Each structure stands twice: as structure tokens, then as C-alpha cells.
Length: 429
Length: 18
Ligand SMILES: O=C(O)CCC(=O)C(=O)O
Ligand SMILES: [Mn+2]
Image 1 (cartoon, helix red, strand yellow):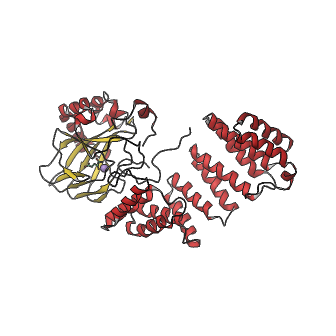
Image 2 (cartoon, helix red, strand yellow):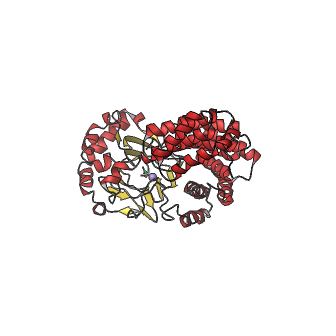
Image 3 (tube, helix red, strand yellow):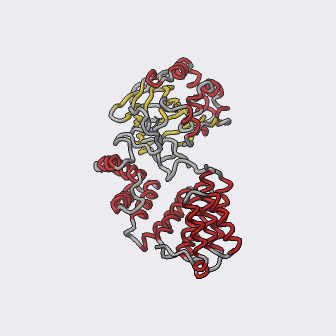
């Protein structure tokens, strides 16, 4: 179907097919020089230049190299600068340049490529969509909101634009507004609406309004391969890992870490209380929209495997103790943090992002009544000087209805069945 | 913006190349 040969490229069509054939055969080295010869002899051929660009692309994948891939990205832009580029070829070339610039994290760059695709093709809705994604990738939810509004002002039936529209509304805590969009969009069946994120957030938005349909959708998404179960709905998983809401210390193998936490708990407690008395701002309010009501704040010492050096100035002995346990200080999918919660607080049901961590809680200051935590079907209480362990990739929930503050210490560990090699390579969360 | 306790961000990992 797609017509990629302007008038002059039709007269050299035999040489261009010759060279693209070598490329399809796998001979990356042969074709790249066959396209570079064509580009030398035909410096205005948009099809020679695209062939060069694609061969650079295949290479940077044979080679897993970032410098050559960066070259393919300029060659893709070279295609669009030439005279008389056929439209199918100009779109294809610049889309790939955006998609491979997103792969490097040049998302400031992928953004400009996408804006140009939309200037050049103002009736293509897919490119307004793909540009909404460019805005979400860099955290610019405001500009992404307009984009999907515009798309919806023109095509209100477009699924993709609807789910993304909802996703934005949910993230803004416009929970009920979010739900028809999330629902109709998943229901459209358009390409790119069958994504776990939308199943996840429709069910969660239903739960918060008290619509008991919410688990119908958790079950749909389980059917279609997004969640491991209806209860355990994390999205950045390593498939297979033993899955259970509550673990005993021995079942994790981290008995040394647990012993240390429990034997040295009072120095951990005392540095946290010192930080509450003299250095409160180190405690930051929870900021993932997880509270229905009340006050909940966290003082973080490690995140994504990296010690916070200024934070460790306010808990120096605790940081020194934990340095001996890399199963937690190098868990690049978890944190190490004090967590304070006061009366009047209800944490919505919610799930962590990854099944690659287990979460330990050490009780530091626990009132006798009013504080409890549910993971899955079972609710439990903290104790001062004692560690509980649960998989926060399962749905969990917390209440604080006591008459003073409740303080715990939270230590994330690598899932025990994860290999040394998985631990070193998995991308941070 | 990061995914610490939940899944509220469009993507939780950061693309940084090969
Ligand atoms: O501080 C708390 O009680 C809440 C912790 C929570 O939701 C978690 O530990 O994943
Ligand atoms: Mn949690």
C-alpha cells in the first residue's frame, strides 16, 4: 500500500530494491554501504536516505549501541529535509525518529518531532494521540490534557483518547469524572486501550466511589494477562515469583536483617523521634493521592537503591546499621523510610507498582488501640520492637483511629527468589 | 515524579538508552 517513491526515485527503483533486499536478508553491513553509495550518487533521494537510516537502526540493535542509534535519528531527520518527500515516507520517517528518541530519553526531543508531525499532518488523529503520550512521558499532564480534549472535540468516539483522558482525570483526583472515560475507552477496543494501567485505575476509581463493579474489571484485566491475580495487580513484574500477601521472617530468608531491626529498634525509634522534635520538615506528606482522609508523612533515607546523604545526617546511627544489609540498601525497586500516621487517617486500598519487593514494617511507637493494616483478606496490627512483612503488590489498606501518633520504620527488600543477576539489571522504580 | 507506594504515573521507569 504505502507509496514512498517520488518521481525521481521511480527511475532508480531497481537499485533501491537491490539494496533494501540485502537489508531484509540480515546483511546489515552490506546494505548500509549499498544505501550509502545510493545516497552519494543521489543526495536528494528520500528513499536512499530512508534506507540508510533504517540500516543504521538495525545496526544499533545488532550492536546495542547508543551512539549509532543517535546517528539513525539524525538520518531519519535528514529524510524529512529533502525535496519532494512522499507523505507516507515523511510520516513513517519522523514517527520512528520520535519512537527511537523516546527510547533514549530525549523526550524533550521526541516532543518536538511529534509537534512537527502534527503541524505537517493536522487531520491525523493518531499523531495527536502519539503526541499526548509524548507529553505524559515527560510528566506534563497539563499539556497532555488539552491534547486529548482537542482530539475529543473532533473525534469523541476515539477510544485511545478516552482512556488517556480518563487516566489524566483519575490522576487529578477527579475520580467520578474519570470513570465513564476509562470505561467507554477500554470498551471501544481500539488499538492501545487494552493496557493494564486503565484496568487498574478504573477499578480503583470505582472502589473509591463505592461502586462494587470495580472487581468485575479487576477480573477482566486478569483474564487478558495484565494482572497476576485479582488481588495482586502490580504492573512491573518478574513472572513466577512466590506470591502471598503475608510472609514470616524465615520464609523470606532475611533473618539477619530482621534480628538486627528487632534488637536495635530503640535507636531507630529515638532518631525518628528526634527528627520529629527538631527537624520535622524532613517528613514529607504522602503525595500519591493514597489518603481518603487525615495526615500521613514519610522521612526517606534510601530510594531506588541510593542513600540520601542529608537525610542520613538526621538518622546517622540508623543509616550506619542498615549499611550492612544490601538486600535492602540496594533494592532499586524499594525504599527505606520512617512513616508517621496520625488519628483520623484512612489509606485507600492500593497496590504497589512491582512484585519484585517485599516490605518490612518495624513498630516504633504503636498506640494500643486504633491502628491496623489489611493486606488482601487479612488484617493485622503492629507491635513495638517487632517486624511484620507483607507483599505490597497485593491490595492493602490502613486505618489510624487512635488518640496519638503512630510511627513505624519501613524497609523494602528484593524478592528472595530473584537472582543476583536480576537484582543488578532490573530498572529502578 | 516517581512510583513509590502506588502506580499513579503514566510510566514508572525512566528510559535512558540500551
Ligand atoms: O505507614 C503506613 O502505615 C502505610 C504503609 C503502606 O501503605 C505501605 O507500607 O505500603
Ligand atoms: Mn502501601
